[PDB]
Image 1 (cartoon, one colour):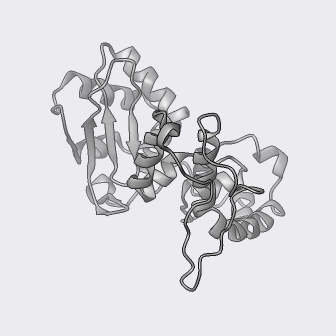
Image 2 (image 1 turned 60 degrees about the vertical axis):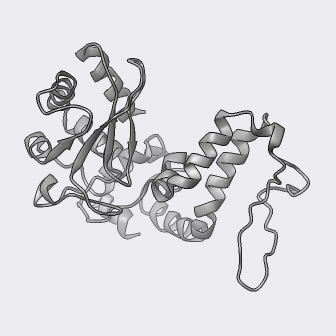
Image 3 (image 1 turned 30 degrees about the vertical axis):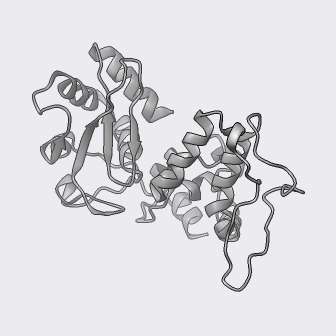
Length: 254
């Protein structure tokens, strides 16, 4: 109710949240990057399972071993799912359903209550046509971020400050509007909150961490992948500024 009234009252709040919260608010399925942020181990296991033909040596049931101290009650992820093993055809289904039920289910009642409070204060139809990244900018505000402050407090890995690829990336960010800058920051960091000190005192999930740009060691057509846990920007090799800026725009817009 408070957030709905704040958006109704055109009021900027300090209510910054994760991706899954707004995704369930917007009824958008939760992506694997959120699970990657909380645990790179399970993300690595899931991407390895999906990429490879693990059906040959799978021998796994659909249900996941979730402990409850006293005794483990088998909570099926689907109807009669214990009798259904993981196969190649539905490996994506298993991965996405495990991602959904690992964190959302223990929070699903809270999200339902928040949706009940929020949707009775704002229109469902007019807002449902937006994305989860735009919801953070809608609620917490669309800040005007300083590219100079960003680049002056940023270290680079795999390149230098005078490297051509890094200069092209910073030129693209300079040409990025407050829309594009905010969405790129959300992609790279996972939040729209701008510290008063700026990128000098930027912090991540694992404590303080200035902005870092890693090398993806991939092809030219490869798209950058960001880890919101460490504020790591995997900037791959590129051939021209146009391809780099198009890739960055596709990554931020998604």
